[PDB]
């Protein structure tokens, strides 16, 4: 499995945090990241999509979020970084179809300017919405990113998204702040090898699966210098919302409301 290099990071002006670097070095076909706000979820996801588009000519993938408005965040970051990386790859051509949320990177057999230049493959990236499942129509994909995955219904993943990955044995990066003990939590446990940890119920006794790898960090784990700035938010955000969005804590919703 191909993975991004230090040089690729440098060309993007990207300096990953420890947790981001872990996600990028993982070759697991199911990566599940439960990280707090500002931990780097969206940036890391966008870097993964850019990596596929340029390093693997003809690669196709989707970013799927609960809504199209949400999908535009990562989709837009990918467009920006693709525009940036294309500057030092003369044999590539970017084509954006903005209203469709469709981004193409054409790969040529020589600098696109040069005489006789022929197209050898076209990589593709689309933004998709779990609340418009009618636009999730029988695709064949190298990769998918599920953004705010804990808010995506499980059936959308199992029926509409996961089967797009079979033919190319593609990967999925499933990232979210947690929303209780739902499918995103169960998928998280399947990849969690870090042992007993506060904020992850049953993390001492979970069954893991070899194609899964899981990553976890509170906002203040990534930015210790911002710890007290985050803690101020406790005062005007409900306890459950704070623990999820900043603590990246898995907590039973009904259990807590007891």
Image (tube, rainbow, N blue to C red):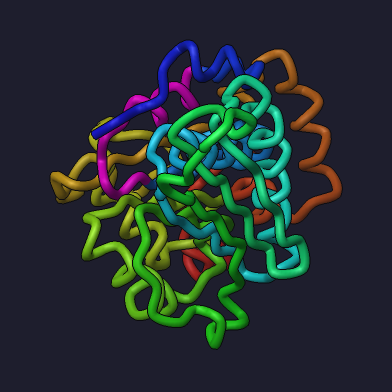
Q: Is residue 81 magenta?
A: no
Q: Is residue 81 left or right of residue 62?
A: right
| Percent coordinates x, y for residue 92 in the rendering | 57, 35
Q: Residue 96: image x %, image y %?
A: 70, 54
Q: Nearer the viewer, residue 64 or 253?
A: 64
Quadrant in the picture for the C terminus: bottom right
- Above or below, 190 against 97 in this view is above
**Foreground residue, 85 or 6?**
85
210 sits left or right of 76 in the view: left
Q: Position of residue 28 (x, y in %)?
A: 25, 40
> Split into 4 quadrants, where in the image is the N terminus?
top left
Where does residue 80 sit, x and y in percent of width and height? 73, 38
First to last magenta residue range: 18-31
Q: Is residue 219 visible?
A: no
Residue under the image location 74 percent in, 20 percent down? 226
Asked whether 110 or 71 is in front, the reply is 110
Q: Residue at x 60, y 16 (%)?
A: 11
Above or below, 150 relative to 143? below
- Check if residue 19 falls in the magenta segment: yes
Residue placed at 50% from the left, 59% from the top? 62
């Amino acid at each position: 499995r191909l993975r991004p290099s230090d040089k690729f990071f440098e060309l993007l002006g990207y300096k990953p945090h420890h947790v981001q670097l872990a996600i990028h070095r993982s070759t697991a076909k199911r990566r599940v990241a439960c990280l707090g706000r500002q931990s780097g979820k969206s940036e890391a996801a966008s870097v993964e999509a850019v990596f596929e588009l340029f390093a693997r000519p003809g690669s196709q993938g989707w970013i799927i979020a609960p809504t199209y408005d949400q999908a535009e965040i990562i989709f837009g970051r990918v467009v920006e970084k693709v525009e940036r990386l294309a500057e030092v790859f003369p044999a590539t051509e970017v084509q954006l179809q903005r209203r469709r949320l469709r981004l193409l990177v054409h790969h040529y057999d020589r600098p696109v300017n040069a005489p006789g230049a022929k197209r050898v493959a076209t990589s593709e990236f689309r933004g998709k919405s779990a609340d418009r499942p009618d636009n999730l129509r029988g695709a064949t994909l190298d990769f998918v990113i599920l953004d705010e995955a804990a808010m995506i219904p499980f059936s959308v993943w199992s029926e509409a998204i996961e089967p797009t990955l079979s033919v190319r044995d593609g990967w999925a990066l499933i990232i979210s702040t947690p929303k209780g003990l739902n499918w995103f939590y169960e998928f998280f446990l399947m990849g969690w090898r870090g042992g007993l940890k506060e904020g992850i119920p049953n993390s001492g006794i979970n069954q893991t699966h070899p194609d899964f790898e899981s990553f976890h960090a509170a906002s203040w784990d990534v930015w210790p210098e911002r710890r007290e700035w985050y803690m101020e938010r406790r005062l005007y955000i409900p306890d459950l919302e704070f623990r999820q969005e900043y603590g990246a804590e898995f907590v039973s919703h009904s259990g807590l409301e007891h």
